[PDB]
Amino acid sequence: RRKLRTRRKVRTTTAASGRLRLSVYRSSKHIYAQIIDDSRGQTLAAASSAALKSGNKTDTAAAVGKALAAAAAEKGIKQVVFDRGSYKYHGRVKALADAAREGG
Amino acid sequence: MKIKLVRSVIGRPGNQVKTVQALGLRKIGDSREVSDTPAVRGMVKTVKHLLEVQE
Amino acid sequence: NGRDSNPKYLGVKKFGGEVVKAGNILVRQRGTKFKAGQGVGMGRDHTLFALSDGKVVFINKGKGARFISIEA
Amino acid sequence: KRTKFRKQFRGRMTGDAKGGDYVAFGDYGLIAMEPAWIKSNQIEACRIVMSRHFRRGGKIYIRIFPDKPVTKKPAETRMGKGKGAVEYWVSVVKPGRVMFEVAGVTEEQAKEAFRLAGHKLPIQTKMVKREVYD
RNA sequence: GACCAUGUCCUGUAGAGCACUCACAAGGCUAAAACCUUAUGAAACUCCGAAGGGGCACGCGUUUAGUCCGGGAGUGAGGCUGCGAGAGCUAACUUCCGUAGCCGAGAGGGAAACAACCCAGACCAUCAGCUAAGGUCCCUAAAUGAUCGCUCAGUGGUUAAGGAUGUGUCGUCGCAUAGACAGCCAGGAGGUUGGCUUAGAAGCAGCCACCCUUCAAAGAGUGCGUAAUAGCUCACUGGUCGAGUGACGAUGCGCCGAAAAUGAUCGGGGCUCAAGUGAUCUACCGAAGCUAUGGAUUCAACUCGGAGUUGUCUGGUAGGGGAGCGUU
RNA sequence: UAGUUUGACUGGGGCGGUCGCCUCCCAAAAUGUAACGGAGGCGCCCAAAGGUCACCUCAAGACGGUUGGAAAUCGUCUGUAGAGCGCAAAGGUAGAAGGUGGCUUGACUGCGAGACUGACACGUCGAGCAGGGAGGAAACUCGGGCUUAGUGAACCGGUGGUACCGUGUGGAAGGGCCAUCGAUCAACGGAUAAAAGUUACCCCGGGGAUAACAGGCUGAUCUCCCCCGAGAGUCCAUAUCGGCGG
RNA sequence: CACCCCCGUGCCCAUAGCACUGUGGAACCACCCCACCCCAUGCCGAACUGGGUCGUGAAACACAGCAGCGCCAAUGAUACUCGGACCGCAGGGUCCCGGAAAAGUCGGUCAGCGCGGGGGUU
Ligand SMILES: [Mg+2]
Ligand SMILES: [Mg+2]
Ligand SMILES: [Mg+2]
Ligand SMILES: [Mg+2]
Ligand SMILES: [Mg+2]
Ligand SMILES: [Mg+2]
Ligand SMILES: [Mg+2]
Ligand SMILES: [Mg+2]
Ligand SMILES: [Mg+2]
Ligand SMILES: [Mg+2]
Ligand SMILES: [Mg+2]
Ligand SMILES: [Mg+2]
Ligand SMILES: [Mg+2]
Ligand SMILES: [Mg+2]
Ligand SMILES: [Mg+2]
Ligand SMILES: [Mg+2]
Ligand SMILES: [Mg+2]
Ligand SMILES: [Mg+2]
Ligand SMILES: [Mg+2]
Ligand SMILES: [Mg+2]
Ligand SMILES: [Mg+2]
Ligand SMILES: [Mg+2]
Ligand SMILES: [Mg+2]
Ligand SMILES: [Mg+2]
Ligand SMILES: [Mg+2]
Ligand SMILES: [Mg+2]
Ligand SMILES: [Mg+2]
Ligand SMILES: [Mg+2]
Ligand SMILES: [Mg+2]
Ligand SMILES: [Mg+2]
Ligand SMILES: [Mg+2]
Ligand SMILES: [Mg+2]
Ligand SMILES: [Mg+2]
Ligand SMILES: [Mg+2]
Ligand SMILES: [Mg+2]
Ligand SMILES: [Mg+2]
Ligand SMILES: [Mg+2]
Ligand SMILES: [Mg+2]
Ligand SMILES: [Mg+2]
Ligand SMILES: [Mg+2]
Ligand SMILES: [Mg+2]
Ligand SMILES: [Mg+2]
Ligand SMILES: [Mg+2]
Ligand SMILES: [Mg+2]
Ligand SMILES: [Mg+2]
Ligand SMILES: [Mg+2]
Ligand SMILES: [Mg+2]
Ligand SMILES: [Mg+2]
Ligand SMILES: [Mg+2]
Ligand SMILES: [Mg+2]
Ligand SMILES: [Mg+2]
Ligand SMILES: [Mg+2]
Ligand SMILES: [Mg+2]
């Protein structure tokens, strides 16, 4: 089964560290990748791909990361924890991290 | 509440002995008035078999 | 027979409603009979000691789901 | 009555019965009045005598069973070393716990069957007929 | 500090349950493991799970202890009882732990007597008073007390399995002024000297099975009988008979069961014409406990330059401390 | 010839057994708690069974299947676990501690706030700081192993560093310190470096703290009685005898 | 929190889960789609994974009905027990006061609260 995600999301015990976590959903390339402060039941920085276009999924993903980096920097955030989903750090998601911390 | 010792403390388990002592009757035939406060009302229920509760 | 082994005075060393210094030991256990909540960190033999000074509180739905947090 | 394999030894105590206060299976039955151990052999004698009264019968459940070993110390020995090895098995029998339960035999026949089956027993007992049963 | 109350947390015992492990009770199902209905035990089994118990905090309440630091010790053989376990034989004035209390270190009243049990912790003095346990017939202090019973056994004043038309209190089942239980006369039947048996077994050794006729009236039918039938009785029938009976049951008090060694006994006398008993209620006796008057110490406050007042305290072994008396 | 050694517990001594550490029950729902009480393990292992990063999910059953068939192996369905965890068990564990690879050694040096535990002495856990490493993209995790056994103070010495003492001064001999090695000293807090019997020729000092006798308490065993009643007694349980049980 | 609905991520922590089942469709999600290479399978693009439309709501998933199952679960009555006070030689047991389960019945539920976004009534 997909015991990848409960495992990786129990390994964010370091939400006790105070950093926010950055969920990603390499599914339909919907890769919405929310930023969450877990303590409240609250999310703070959405970046859904509704009509961003940008072409092939591996590069639209980096576009989603570079746009969300601004979308969260507006509110005043910089500590980061990359709560990957079940997905590997394989590239199409790795571009999201590269472009996200390229412009925190 | 009126209280009077009419039982010896001898030979009775030591919680009852420190209970009568803090009640402040050190000898049988002692009496005293007492507050209605639940703390002391339970202090007297604990050793009611030693005392004559009057009120 | 006639053999036996030393006591290991294990337990809930600090009960909920007890202020604790950092590094106080609060539960002793063979394993994770307690699973350590926020502020607490669990050692090698799975004793869990508070990291932060404050009150001790028990999260406890039970059945292996009992956790010890500390509130400042 | 003997238990085919176990762990070796036990202990003892008593308080009133919580398993088998009501009869099933049979027509009539018999109940303890006194707490006690009962040996395998006391059972087997009740079986022998109630099978004497029940020729070609087959209505003899034995709703009790020697579970507990009890181990006397050997010949003449001063104390020291274990409980020897088990000398006989016994069944705890607290009051109100049924022992016996017949069917298919008329009231006075079961009544005599229970007379003899109790007289070999080390306890008071009583015959009962079933009706206040859920 | 200590007890007690509130708040909170932690626990896996009693109990209780089979959901796992071992065990185990009657069946159905089936190449029997498995499975289902039903049924159970478990120190090393737990789906559960109190009472209590421990830590914290408060004191929202009565009390007086505690903590550390320095001098001196002794003790490191425990004993019983009750509760909870182990070991034992559910033995022991047994042995080993937990726990409470007494004894050790404890006087006084009770238990005839008696470290441990029940009452009650002795500062001193009194020819003063109330009580505790326990008592009130004489010994022997104090009701031959009162009221409803219970037991006629000296039970009381030594056990049990088991028996008993012993006796009260309720209580369940039948058949009766269309007249029953014992109780007297009257009948005892039919194939049938019934199948199944050993050598004969024929109400009436005994394994297997009980229907059918003639009847106001009787079961191929009870215990006896010689080895078999008769034989006197019985279960239904009847003139009489004239009113209750018989059954298992719960129980209260008793009987038997119930033999040991120098001489008997409840402590003794004696007790039912209660001095036994269960239920109630008083009235008094009854301690070195409590109260009264007097008296002195330990401590502490309170006053004057140990004294005195008020409170309080004063059983005591090893021991620690303190004030003093006697001899050279 | 001589001076000595020759262990303790022990329902009396001897014999047998035991002596240290771990697990469970006893242990009476805190911690603790005895027994020659009931059960069983340890005197090690692992260059990866570590650190880290990443990835898989186990028994067992049924239907189906090649030489195998109750159980090799593959295939489907059910499958909070009925498996596994190096050895014993309890706890624990399914988001892993179980299984499988890549990298490397934190199986580091210097420290230790705070506590748990113990009469001590030992023992346990431990956040975070330095120097510097290792894995990861990072958060982060590493100063051994899921945990609890795998162990012995102190003395006297071996080996490598270091440059403190080193006797008049300079050196060296020797010593100190840091590291490490030598222990069934297992009677496992460990009397010496170095040790067995025997006494009925016995002697002393003690003990009813403790056996042989006798009394006592108990009454398993012993002696006796009673209940039942199977059968024996042709017949008929009880004239006698009375199984198995109480 | 205008009304629904979807993707995700929390709190909760079986009264939320199972099964039977019906709705769902290019809006969302999901399989199918191809593989020399990023990247990978101790064999397989099944899994990760990279390049995408059709197709299809089949399967999975979401959401409703659903009391066969599970899950919860009284009251009442006990068991037991703190203190008090008793009987039995003994195993054992009783009484007064107060605390009081477990099992079972009665009955309850196929949940309940957020946060961000996506597309709807245009
Ligand atoms: Mg018990
Ligand atoms: Mg039951
Ligand atoms: Mg043994
Ligand atoms: Mg206080
Ligand atoms: Mg039990
Ligand atoms: Mg306790
Ligand atoms: Mg305060
Ligand atoms: Mg001192
Ligand atoms: Mg001693
Ligand atoms: Mg003792
Ligand atoms: Mg025994
Ligand atoms: Mg003794
Ligand atoms: Mg002794
Ligand atoms: Mg003494
Ligand atoms: Mg004393
Ligand atoms: Mg006395
Ligand atoms: Mg006496
Ligand atoms: Mg006298
Ligand atoms: Mg004496
Ligand atoms: Mg004396
Ligand atoms: Mg005595
Ligand atoms: Mg008394
Ligand atoms: Mg008087
Ligand atoms: Mg009186
Ligand atoms: Mg007189
Ligand atoms: Mg009797
Ligand atoms: Mg009179
Ligand atoms: Mg009077
Ligand atoms: Mg007097
Ligand atoms: Mg006096
Ligand atoms: Mg005076
Ligand atoms: Mg004194
Ligand atoms: Mg005094
Ligand atoms: Mg004195
Ligand atoms: Mg010796
Ligand atoms: Mg304990
Ligand atoms: Mg002791
Ligand atoms: Mg791991
Ligand atoms: Mg650290
Ligand atoms: Mg570092
Ligand atoms: Mg790196
Ligand atoms: Mg050297
Ligand atoms: Mg030596
Ligand atoms: Mg030693
Ligand atoms: Mg000589
Ligand atoms: Mg002497
Ligand atoms: Mg002696
Ligand atoms: Mg002797
Ligand atoms: Mg002899
Ligand atoms: Mg109730
Ligand atoms: Mg009470
Ligand atoms: Mg009690
Ligand atoms: Mg009650």
Image (spheres, coloured by chain):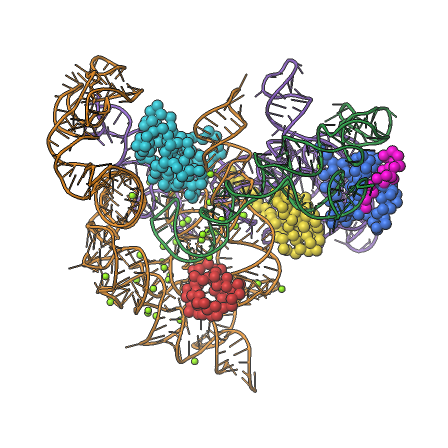
Chain colours: A blue, B red, C yellow, D cyan, E orange, F purple, G green
Note whether residue D44 is visible: no
* Number of marks in picture: 0
In front here: F230 or F15? F230
> Is residue A56 in the magenta section?
yes
Nearest the viewer among E327 and E100 is E100
Which region of the structure is painted magenta? A45-64
Which residue is drawn at the image coordinates 53% and 63% (left, top)?
B39
Q: Residue at x 63, y 53 (%)?
A: C16
Residue E247, compared with residue E84, is above or below; it is above
What secondary structure do most residues of the magenta stretch adopt?
loop
Q: Position of residue E150 (x, y in %)?
A: 25, 52
Q: Does residue F26 appear left or right of residue E146 in this picture?
A: right
Q: Residue G79's spot in the image, x, y percent?
A: 45, 46
- Quadrant in which the C terminus of chain B appears: bottom left
The residue that appears at 87% across and 43% down in the rendered structure is A67
Question: Of A24 and F199, which appears nearest the observer?
Answer: A24
| Left or right of residue G74, residue E115 in this image | left
Residue C4 belongs to the span the image colors magenta:
no
Tell me: residue F238, above or below residue E79. Answer: above
Quadrant in the picture for residue C21: bottom right
Which quadrant holds residue F52?
top right
In the foreground, E324 or E295 = E295
Residue drawn at x 49%, y 68% is: B34
